[PDB]
Image (spheres, coloured by chain):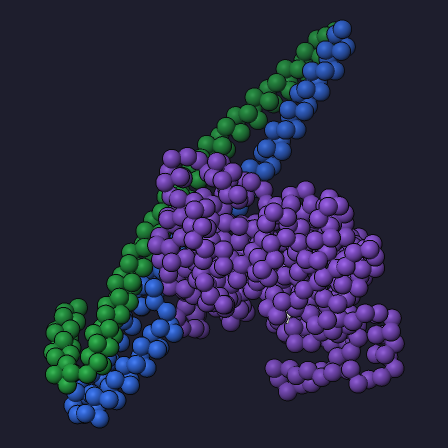
Chain colours: A purple, B blue, C green
């Protein structure tokens, strides 16, 4: 009798509690139809959401509600919530308690307004919200350590001790899988092709999801690519065309590793992780080294864990051993963390009752959220 | 709560049961199939009614929303002008007071 | 409509037939109609909940907009007062120079 769902900047997921996978996951997009004449279509709706928006994107104008893990609008956000509850899930919002994710270090005003929208327009019985990173960590069973929540839109290096995140140690970076899509498009253009529309963006992200490579030394990788053409792998098109792929496969995470190729003036992922652990006190640094996880949609690249291991060892003192994990299903680890947290007898104690909102304003509730 | 997989599995069980009862005697299976189809059409009508209710809710939500982005922009520009006037007032206060001393 | 009650009676008599056949399958037949009724009630409750959500959202957006125009009026009045203060202090400085 519980529901859990995400706030992903893209490809948002939703499902019940105590399950191995979300019930339904769909792009987090809302859009309205433009004003025209003869409706050439059947079964039209008010404002299509998610998969319907993807299917009929050519006849819609759409606005993404959540940017870099932070939701800009609120009307679009509640539209998404309505769509999830009443189309994909067919569930009563008044009935079940609901658990919701939360981007690390969000403004108190944003959190409190989000809770009040959850509770007033929906009249939910008892709603709770937790940070995505803690759930992602708990997904791998680990209770302390560093988490590289490198999701779509935003990346967050977050360490955890005592089972809860460290506020002052949290670091933020706006590197994104969408940024990687832009990099892949640019690379494919100087290879020479035509990719400018949103359908072409969809094709590009499909290509990158199907094919990518993470290796150790980009110099020797490029040398091998220019010498031999065996790794020059082919890929289909929706129409009968065949496009062959080279160095861009290795370039897909090179921009992740060194933001200078995109000119972000930031540092690499390994650099950010090392900076975060240095911000951490020297006591639990060995345990944080032993507990390294990669949770996020972008953390699915093949052979990335070993590269992060090499980089952190190189930039770390040699005296202590590291340990980086790579769960088989890292994308949904937030959903699994939410589900396992919900399916706990003691967790029912930390719910936020409707009566509490009735008796007091949500400020003390934002305090209680811990 | 309702679940498509639950509905599909129960439909499969109903098919197996109607197969058994038809093997017993076919007319009972004919009646059971007709009853199955009739509440199937009833639930289809109920689902259509619910979808209509959802469409009503979202349509009226848009109607009540009706813009206000220019409103928020007006909020921003007006408070900016307010703080500008505040700072100018304090600056002139300081300048004139110092000249007076 | 009204066909449903007669259909329920006929299906219960079909249950009588299948339970004079008297197999454990009859218990399954009692269950399938139970979940038919369950999903019917769920559809009705979800419909009413959708209507309630609609009206509640209308109320919330209306109250938010109302306090919005209150803020508009107060801020405009503050702008007018601050402008007046600007001219007043300009004149004060000029008079001090004189
Ligand atoms: N096979 C794949 N390999 C690598 N990356 C992928 C793959 N499939 C999808 N992605 C990336 O994962 C991203 C979305 O992942 P996910 O939904 O887990 O994170 P998110 O919740 O959107 O991020 P955030 O929480 O920061 O908003 C997409 O931007 C996409 O580029």
B60 sits left or right of A274 in the view:
left
Q: Is residue C19 visible?
A: yes
Image point 85% across, 84% down: which residue?
A228
- Is A88 above or below relative to A135? below
Q: Judge whether A177 appears above or below A129 on screen.
A: below
Measuring 25% from the left and 63% from the top, which residue is drawn there?
Answer: C41
The residue shown at (15%, 83%) is C22
Q: Is residue A189 left or right of residue A27?
A: right
| Residue C86 appears left or right of A128 | right
Which image quadrant for residue B72?
A: top right
Q: Tell me where residue A230 sits by quadrant.
A: bottom right
In this rendering, is residue B64 above or below A367? below
Can you give x and y, in whole percent of width and height, for residue A113 in the image?
Answer: 49, 43
Ligand 1 appears in which quadrant?
bottom right
Residue A57: x, y in percent? 54, 68
Residue under the point 69% across and 15% down: B93
Foreground pick, A161 / A85:
A161
Q: The N terminus of chain A is located in which quarter?
A: bottom left
Most foreground residue, A332 or A211:
A332
> Horizontal and vertical percent for residue A174?
69, 54
């Amino acid at each position: 009798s519980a529901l859990v769902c995400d706030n992903g900047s893209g490809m948002v997921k939703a499902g019940f509690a105590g399950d191995d996978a979300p019930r339904a996951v769909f792009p987090s997009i809302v859009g309205r139809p433009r004003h025209t004449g003869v409706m050439v279509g059947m079964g039209q709706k008010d404002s299509y959401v998610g998969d319907e928006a993807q299917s009929k994107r050519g006849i819609l104008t759409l606005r993404y509600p959540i940017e870099h893990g932070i939701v800009t609008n609120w009307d679009d956000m509640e539209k998404i919530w309505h769509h999830t509850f009443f189309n994909e899930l067919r569930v009563a919002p008044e009935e079940h308690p609901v658990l919701l994710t939360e981007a690390p270090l969000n403004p108190k005003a944003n959190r409190e307004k989000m809770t009040q929208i959850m509770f007033e327009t929906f009249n939910v019985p008892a709603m709770y919200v937790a940070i995505q990173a803690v759930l992602s960590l708990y997904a791998s069973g680990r209770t302390t350590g560093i988490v590289l929540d490198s999701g779509d839109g935003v990346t967050h290096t977050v360490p955890i001790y005592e089972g809860y995140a460290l506020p002052h140690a949290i670091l933020r970076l706006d590197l994104a899988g969408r940024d990687l899509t832009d990099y892949l498009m640019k690379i494919l253009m100087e290879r020479g092709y035509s990719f400018t529309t949103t359908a072409e963006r969809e094709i590009v992200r499909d290509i990158k999801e199907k094919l990518c490579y993470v290796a150790l030394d980009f110099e020797q990788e490029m040398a091998t690519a220019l010498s031999s053409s065996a790794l020059e792998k082919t890929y289909e098109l929706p129409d009968g065309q065949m496009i062959t792929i080279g160095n861009e496969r290795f370039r897909c995470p090179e921009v992740l590793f060194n933001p200078n190729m995109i000119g972000m003036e930031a540092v690499g992922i390994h650099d950010t992780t090392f900076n975060s652990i240095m911000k951490c006190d020297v006591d639990i640094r060995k345990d944080l080294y032993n507990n390294i996880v990669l949770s996020g949609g972008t953390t699915m690249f093949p052979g990335i864990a070993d590269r992060m291991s090499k980089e952190i060892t190189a930039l770390a003192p040699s005296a202590m051993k590291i340990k980086v994990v790579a769960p088989p299903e890292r994308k949904y680890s937030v959903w699994i963390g939410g589900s396992i947290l919900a399916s706990l007898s003691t967790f029912q104690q930390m719910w936020i009752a409707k009566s509490e909102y009735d008796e007091s304003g949500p400020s003390i509730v934002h305090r209680k959220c811990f | 709560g309702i679940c498509p997989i639950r509905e599909e599995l129960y439909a499969q069980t109903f098919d197996e049961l109607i197969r058994q009862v038809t093997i017993n005697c076919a007319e009972r299976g004919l009646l059971l199939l007709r009853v199955r189809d009739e509440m199937r059409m009833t639930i289809a009508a109920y689902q259509t009614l619910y979808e209509s209710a959802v469409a009503f809710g979202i349509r009226k939500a848009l109607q009540t929303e009706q813009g206000k982005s220019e409103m928020e922009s007006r909020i921003t520009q007006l408070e900016g002008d307010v703080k500008d006037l505040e700072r100018q007032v304090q600056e002139w206060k300081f300048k004139c007071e110092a000249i007076e001393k």
